[PDB]
Image: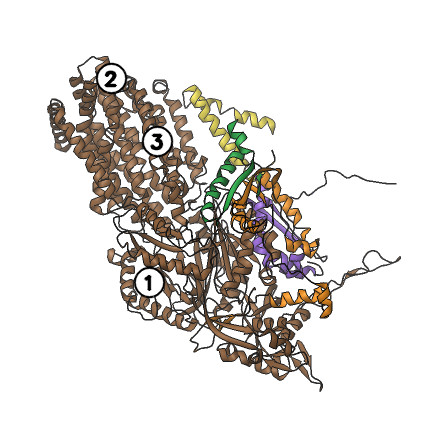
Amino acid sequence: YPGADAETVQNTVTQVIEQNMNGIDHLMYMSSNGDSTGTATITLTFESGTDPDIAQVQVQNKLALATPLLPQEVQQQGISVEKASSSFLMVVGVIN
Amino acid sequence: MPNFFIDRPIFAWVIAIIIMLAGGLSILKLPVAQYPTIAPPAISITAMYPGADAETVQNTVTQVIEQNMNGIDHLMYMSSNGDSTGTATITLTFESGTDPDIAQVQVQNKLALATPLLPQEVQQQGISVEKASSSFLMVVGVINTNGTMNQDDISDYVAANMKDPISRTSGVGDVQLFGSQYAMRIWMDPNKLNNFQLTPVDVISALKAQNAQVAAGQLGGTPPVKGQQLNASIIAQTRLTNTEEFGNILLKVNQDGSQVRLRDVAKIELGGESYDVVAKFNGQPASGLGIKLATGANALDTANAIRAELAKMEPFFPSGMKIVYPYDTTPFVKISIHEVVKTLVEAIILVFLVMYLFLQNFRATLIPTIAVPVVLLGTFAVLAAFGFSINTLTMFGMVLAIGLLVDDAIVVVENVERVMAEEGLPPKEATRKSMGQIQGALVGIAMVLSAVFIPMAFFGGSTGAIYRQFSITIVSAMALSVLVALILTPALCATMLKPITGFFGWFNRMFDKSTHHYTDSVGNILRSTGRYLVLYLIIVVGMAWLFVRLPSSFLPDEDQGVFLSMAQLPAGATQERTQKVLDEMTNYYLTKEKDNVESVFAVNGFGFAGRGQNTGIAFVSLKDWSQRPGEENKVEAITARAMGYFSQIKDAMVFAFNLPAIVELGTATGFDFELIDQGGLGHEKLTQARNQLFGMVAQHPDVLTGVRPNGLEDTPQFKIDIDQEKAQALGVSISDINTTLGAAWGGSYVNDFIDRGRVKKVYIMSEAKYRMLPEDIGKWYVRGSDGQMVPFSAFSTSRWEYGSPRLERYNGLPSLEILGQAAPGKSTGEAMALMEELAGKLPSGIGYDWTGMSYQERLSGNQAPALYAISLIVVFLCLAALYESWSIPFSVMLVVPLGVVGALLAATFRGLTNDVYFQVGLLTTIGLSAKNAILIVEFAKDLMEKEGKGLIEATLEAVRMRLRPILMTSLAFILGVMPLVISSGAGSGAQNAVGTGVMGGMVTATILAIFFVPVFFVVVRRRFS
Amino acid sequence: GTDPDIAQVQVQNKLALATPLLPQEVQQQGISVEKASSSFLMVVGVINTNGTMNQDDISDYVAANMKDPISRTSGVGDVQLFGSQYAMRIWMDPNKLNNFQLTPVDVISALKAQNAQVAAGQLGGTPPVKGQQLNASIIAQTRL
Amino acid sequence: LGIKLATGANALDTANAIRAELAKMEPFFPSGMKIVYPYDTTPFVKIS
Amino acid sequence: ERLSGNQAPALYAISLIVVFLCLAALYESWSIPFSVMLVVPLGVVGAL
């Protein structure tokens, strides 16, 4: 949500999405945060064993009922849903 | 096995204990819901186009989405409709059993690619893709006792401080809101706008620019200048929040020098997003949340949590609010579940008492009391393995199985009891000999019964979903019972049993006399087998004659405590007139039925058939069952009284009706017809065809009855014609008239704003008093090229014409929903087929198609005889294996008509129907009518083959041996399921259907079988030497 | 062996991050993400014995009344059409346009202004004023 | 119409359904119009 | 880490019982398994 303070992005974007994301199958805990840059990322952690591919479908499916309520600007930017990993597998440094 | 565990009692207990623990653990994890998934998955695509006529939602929204719905897997039929309020839905029904989650995302994805094609307003309002198959767990409604705030305030509060905690509760899979939060509403004023030389386009432009947001970036963000020491983000113009701040929006600066602010040209207030629906509660404003249930969560538990969380926030409600629950399904589930456990515990007591009446020893009656519960707990583990969930179907599919469980415990124990007393063998050795007589038969019973219930599970459509619940429960329970009757009961019998006046002394004396007389009667019959074979034909025709005469239904209706009440007003009736009917409709319930009706959720402007200002609903909630004694205060009686009174109402087609048994589906009674327009003739020509069909079904009043439309008849509608030539002459852009006309009257959604930590819409719309009559069109002014305003009367011609407030489509082509039902005494198959012939002579290019239940019945009906051709043959093969012959199995199969006759006679006399419960009711009677016959024959064959006794002598001994275990099975089972017939309280519609079919069938199955199986065995054996 | 349906979701999930960046003309025409092999399963030809219809009148009927149901039948990924559905063609005349001092931009504006169908609210729609007695939808110009 | 096959779907099962769908459209064809199948590989999956 | 500790008592309680049932089945007595299940504390104390 470009050009949005941390307080405003938290109240408008994250609050709306986080409301319409409770009730997924095998939901363990839900974390979210929005920073001054305007990026508001929500990370869901499913119960160990849930088929990760299917979990994305449910999360992606539910987000559709929430996209209209977000500010008009957010829709243009687009919302990305993809399985996330906390730490790097490796790093490939390039030097001259 | 029986001879392996007999001397290994401990190893039997361990397997019994493991099974018991499996049930205990799985009882605490199994989901509980009123019904399982029955209806096929359905996806609804709702799109709002504010202030749009009925046609427009079709030619720009519904059609465009339909054209782009390509390449979706397992799509069964697509239907849609666009009403006059701007809302169009496209319900896609998929194949039964398809993963709904994958189905929904596929439907959404195609919509996502087609979103750009839709108009700008539709995209701005957003298109919602939901699941329509699921049903509400409960509908919690909040009211306003003091009447100090309208529904909008209540709806806004609910969306802000009640929707969050409820949606975070355990098991709440989806929360819907029956309202709209606040939305800054701007009430324009044509009189004031013309004074200041303004137009609605100017108002829109100012709002779109003076409530925006900016990305100021950073102060000293990368890349910096060398030596920087500070870095902080920049905050630029931010949205407005106060209604006063909106008023100050500067709209125009007069040439003189004065200011023209918005507040001086339009009233501003916090209103609702939509005033289409006006909810009420006993005459007070209200709004509610439609709480659904997540997949795999205790329905009883979740409704307990929700009612507990709302107790936390009870003090925090602003003074005047209160929480009410017009519609809830967990109280009914509580009754429908406990009533079953009251039967599964009454059967155990009855079996304990029944055996104690015959055997007269405590140690004997303790063997079933430990062998029946082990199976009941065991089947839960097997039931939980397949993923099933406790519900009204499986439970009523398990009360039917209690008969199977008992007869697999009475036979094993009773036979052992007979041997000890006749042969005198010790308890540890009597079981070895006793189980040597029926170990083969019991294993055979498992296959034969497994060959009668398994085919039921292979049906298709909605019926297959209901049948699959009964078959798996009965099969699982039956399979375990045989296993637990071959592993555990023999161990208990030997270990527990011991070697061997008043009432019991008299009873034995009388019973001994009876059984001796019974053998005399069969002896007389077997000498004249020819005469009694005639009676077997006079009984089979009776079965066939009565079976056809039995009406066919789907599921019985039950007093769920809530019943709807439609309300339809003539064409064009406004909101005020409807609310007058909905008030005298709510007054009757609270005046003539004050002792039964609890509340009336008098919704307005909403209807199932259609939507508009001339429709209404009232979810009437009745008092608890305990406060409604007798049949005079049931839903069936109350609806009849209300229907009689509402026939006197003028200017309203009011009519009340009870909910369906499974609210997820529709009525599921009758037929569903689509009158497609294949040739592109147009809507007007299509209606001419429907009227032709309606005027031609009248020739067949004895087959088709109550054939009515489901849409809305065309009604007058204002038509405004913009004279293109005149507009150019006066220098007014046609793109400006379309906005002033479309924004002043239809309302527009300019942009969003932030308030109290939430984002809310801003709507502009003319004041209510300036957009009412046709004369008001001339009251609106639009700026010309030179700045001089012109009125709509100068370049607009208006006239009244007819149109359809609710257009409809089907599979992409126009249609006209037609509903109805078959005439009394005529099957839906003939009524359904008659319509095809009638619809086949309509003008060219007008086809048809069956949807809803009829489309499913057009597929399930094919498998009705085919599945029982496999079942009958496989059963015969199993029997031929058990008896080691081809001719003997005829005797076993021929008792099937005996069992059915009792059920049909009882059902017909009680005036029941051939519903789903009854059909399963026959199977257990048929299943438990052969289980008593398979042992009579196998004993006769055993005696004849080993001891060599003559045929007639062998059969007489066989019937004498098996007279006790037949009676205790029938006497205990009939007494066990007698409560289910006398029951008249909550959830009695299902209980009566199951109870009557079983008790009636069992009585004639027991009486006739013990007189006929010996006749069949001798006749079959005689002829097939 | 990859689940073909799960693959499409991920492919189209990523495509939704780039669709806004595409030119408007592409979005209006519509971009379809199909899961179909490049080889044709079969071809359903259509002809007319009379011969009155040309290679386009037949094409319209295939698209109008036949193409849509086929593309939805379970087990069909893509249904290409060997022709073109009808579409009102405006054959412009540069010799005449210059004569009347016009341009294609003016013609585009005229089509959007006049061949446009506008939502027009209702007569006394909600919220009404006490004493109302009639409610009828308003209709303005529609698609030509 | 050049019909393609969705990945993972049976070739002969789909072709059986498509020929069933057209049967519901043949009756309403205007005068002269007729359906001819100039190319289909499914029969080879059946005759073979 | 918290979840590991919470379900630890159930893991030992249910594993001990299953052995008792499995031992009793093999030894056809409710006492001899009670004479082999009394050595586990002599084993656990070794690990601690």
Mark 3 vs 1, N-terminal side: 3
The chain drawn in yellow is E
Q: Are marks 1 and 2 in contact (CB under 8 Å)?
A: no
Tell me the distance, in whole angstroms, between the alpha carbons under discs 3 and 1. 47 Å
Mark 3 vs 2, N-terminal side: 3
Mark 1 vs 2, N-terminal side: 1
Q: Which scheme is used to colour this image of the protein?
A: by chain
Q: Is residue B971 above or below residue B820?
A: above
User: What is the crowding at mark 2: few (fewer than 14 residues within 10 Å), some, or many (at least 20)?
Assistant: some
Q: Amino acid at mark 2?
A: Asp
> Which part of the image, by quadrant, shows the C terminus of chain B?
top left
Q: Nearer the viewer, residue A8 or B555?
A: B555
The chain drawn in purple is A
Tell me the distance, in whole angstroms, between the alpha carbons under discs 3 and 2. 25 Å
User: With B748 as the anchor, is B446 left or right in this view?
Assistant: left
Q: Nearer the viewer, residue B65 or B848?
A: B848
| Callouts 3 and 1 on one subunit | yes
Q: Name the residue that disc number 3 marks.
A: B478
Which tint is chain C? orange
**Which label sits on residue B655?**
1
Q: Position of residue B87 (x, y in %)?
A: 51, 61
User: With B674 as the anchor, is B920 left or right in this view?
Assistant: left
The chain drawn in green is D
User: What is the crowding at mark 3: few (fewer than 14 residues within 10 Å), some, or many (at least 20)?
Assistant: many
| Callouts 3 and 2 on one subunit | yes
Q: Is residue B737 above or below residue D23?
A: below
Q: Quadrant of residue B26?
A: top left
